[PDB]
Amino acid sequence: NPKAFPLADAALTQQILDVVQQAANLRQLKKGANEATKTLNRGISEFIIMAADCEPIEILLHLPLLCEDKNVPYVFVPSRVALGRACGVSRPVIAASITTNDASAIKTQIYAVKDKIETLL
Amino acid sequence: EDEEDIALEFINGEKKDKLVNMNSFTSMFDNIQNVQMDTFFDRVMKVLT
Amino acid sequence: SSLSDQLAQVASNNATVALDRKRRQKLHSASLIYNSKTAATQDYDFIFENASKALEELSQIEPKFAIFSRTLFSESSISLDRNVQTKEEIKDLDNAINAYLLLASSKWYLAPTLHATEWLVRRFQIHVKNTEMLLLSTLNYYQTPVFKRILSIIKLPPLFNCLSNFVRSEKPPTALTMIKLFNDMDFLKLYTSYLDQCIKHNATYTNQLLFTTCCFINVVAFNSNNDEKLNQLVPILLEISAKLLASKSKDCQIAAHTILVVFATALPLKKTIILAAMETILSNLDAKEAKHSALLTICKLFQTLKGQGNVDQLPSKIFKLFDSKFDTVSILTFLDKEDKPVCDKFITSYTRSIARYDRSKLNIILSLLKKIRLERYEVRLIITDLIYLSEILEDKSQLVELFEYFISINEDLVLKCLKSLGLTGXXXXXX
Amino acid sequence: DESDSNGDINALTKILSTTYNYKDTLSNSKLLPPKKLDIVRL
Amino acid sequence: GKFRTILIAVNAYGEVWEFDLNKNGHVIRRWKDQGGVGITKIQVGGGTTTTCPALQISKIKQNRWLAVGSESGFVNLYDRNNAMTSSTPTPVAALDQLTTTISNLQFSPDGQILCMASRAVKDALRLVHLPSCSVFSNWPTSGTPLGKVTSVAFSPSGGLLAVGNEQGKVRLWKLNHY
Amino acid sequence: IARVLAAKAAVSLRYDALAEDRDDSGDIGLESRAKVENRLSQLEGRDLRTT
Amino acid sequence: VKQHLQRETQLKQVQQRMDAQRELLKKGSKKKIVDSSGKISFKWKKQRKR
């Protein structure tokens, strides 16, 4: 979609969806569009992964509106069937949100990805 | 061509048919009321194919 | 057995016999229209006025109810109780009321049938004696408020034990519980013997005949796992669809197509059964709208089976019958439909039958193949027959143009069948 | 009253009378049936 | 008398490469699997594969089914007649009956059955019928002894089925159709 | 149904507040309502009683 | 407002240790690991919940 903004490449998408698959093992990951909207308002979101091929795309465009206010990074992985399978859930997931836990073992690997997402912004 | 090699055309020649599973026709009751029999039969054939 | 088991068996046989006044004020108080207090305070003479006034309105809607005013709804038929009469005379009271609930069941949304059957409820006790043909005539109105009243009277038979939790319930009996009725192997054997009784009088109506199949589809659907259960099921269902094709009515015939196509996809039937079914679809196929549904059966029936003899030539009595009811131009307008159903495994049995039986019209046999992308083995199995035909038939130039279509596409397929049978140079030398 | 003495209408009833098992198991189809897999552990 | 062989390599992210070995190794085409993030195994089938190979050169037949494993149970079936056109093809059916990492995808030698197994959870072989993409429901039951299935194999000829475990016991079956 | 509406009404609202092109025929919304009617008539067919 | 910032960050950690306790009950196969520091966290098995 042309409404898609910052859309990660083929390369960084493999890094983002690997951290998603490791955050769903630590259960540190809230799932879905209507739950990633929650973690923004609580402020406990590290960053926001979203899908690009969701039809209609307008059902998740409020998250780039919301993240610009609260200064939380966001990208678009290209396909919602991908982010679904990497999240541990049978249904396709169109927006995924990494929560903040500083005791996490994967904290280092999140901030490596987070810096690359703020690089696109 | 061998006799078993003929049958691999007969195996590959079939196509996938959508099956009849136990939850496939239970929604048809909501549209029985005052419909013509022609337009119901296509609503069966649209499920099977 | 015990005493109280045998002594409650006498209670069923005297369920209608009014003995005490309190026994009468329980039996007479239940009815279709009036509530329990105002029903017990009125004569049969009062009810007969409202019935015979209403029944003359139903005679105006259709003249078939005019006969029952001579026999059941007559003024002399107030004094007759069921219990007083002999055993032969009761079966005639059943066979009148069984003939009545066929004609009554169609006009059941209308207000006058509610006032009409109620005298035949309250005087003739059909809510106790014969509640099968009362309920089987009115089994398709389960969502309506009139069937909720019919449940609020009837002591349910042992076969309708699925609805027994919905008697005097608030909400209507839901759509799945209607399927749990038809899932039983015995309750179907009523609904056969109700329907073959209902076709013989040629009063089968559209909303009724949908609700038959919309249950008969689901019974095949709920039993699509248990291959034993389906094996004992089609003496019940296919014997309907055999008799449901014998109907003059075009509307009954389309219902037979819905059950046949659904069962054929759920269970691979034998070759002889499908060719049997294809004759009876062909034989009584008269009206316009029954023909379109009938063609999508044979389109779908031939793809259900798969095995040796899958693509066999049609038998002689079958094929010319299919040419009689379906035209070779009309089958071409069928393939050009943008629906474009999977006509794949049938036409390669249709084309081979042309090659053996008729042979006069092989211009069509080219134009059949441009319109359908066939399967790989089918084209080989066609071209073997034509090369047999190439030697036998007195040689013809239009047959040469058929192979020119196969010199266009799949050249090696033409070679490999010739390298299986005959020579490579001899076919081009033959033409 | 009863004695036995275009295609017919009774063609579907007659062949149902003359068969007792309806599923095509006699074919040796060489196509595999869905949902029911004949297997024998060795 | 003449055929060419083709590599089908899999990126972990899900990009399928198509090298051909007859001429020196060049890409023929690329196509991404729809979805498929953490991908373990691909094996093609329906013809001659490395499990059900050929005898003479005329026996070599082009395959028809392609299956793509995952680390989340997802198998994706590709009809090889249609998927070679668009180069970003839609898979036919997304099989998701397993719950863990796929570790063995082998076909029948006739190309009608797709095994799929996981070496993580015990008793985790599932058979998939083709082309209907319906998992078989009767076998395997609960009481079908498998163990942690680590190695599945079909016969080329007789229709047998050999399933390994972690315990060491190779338990053998017979597809009674064949 | 109060979940399924408030989900699909949240799907319908973001197509209305945040689409600069509107087909203005309720084309997403009638696709939303048909999913709830499928959810509803599924959920009325199921019943807690024993048959 | 110095105290609210001291109140809230203390009050978030009550949720963070409660939310981790609430996520132990649901499904899945859990691994009891202990760090070398002594803090207890869990690691659920890589298994797509259905």
Image: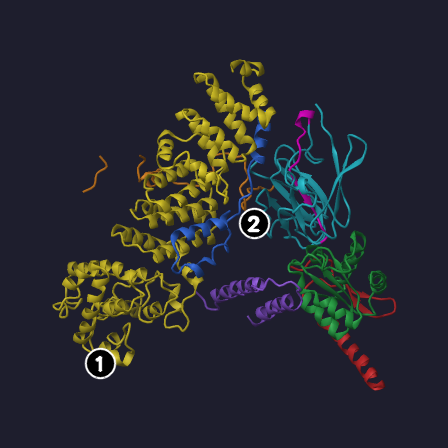
Q: Residues within 10 Å of mark 2 (few under 14, many from 20)?
A: some
Q: Which mark is in front, 1 or 2?
A: 1
The secondary structure type at the circle numbered 1 is loop
Q: Was residue E56 drawn as part of the magenta stretch in this picture?
A: yes
User: Relative to A104, is C424 above or below?
Assistant: above
Q: Residues within 10 Å of mark 1 (few under 14, many from 20)?
A: few
- Taking depth in this image into account, of C77 and C349 the one nearest to the observer is C349
The secondary structure type at the circle numbered 2 is loop
Q: Colour of chain E?
A: cyan
Q: Are discs 1 and 2 less than 8 Å apart at CB? A: no
- In the picture, which chain is green? A
Q: Name the kind of residue labelled 1 in the image.
A: Thr
Q: Residue at x 30, y 44 (%)?
A: C246
In the image, which residues are magenta?
E55-71
Q: Colour of chain D?
A: orange
Q: Which residue is mark 2?
A: E137
Q: Colour of chain G?
A: red
Q: Which corner quadrant holds the N terminus of chain E? A: top right
Q: Colour of chain B?
A: blue
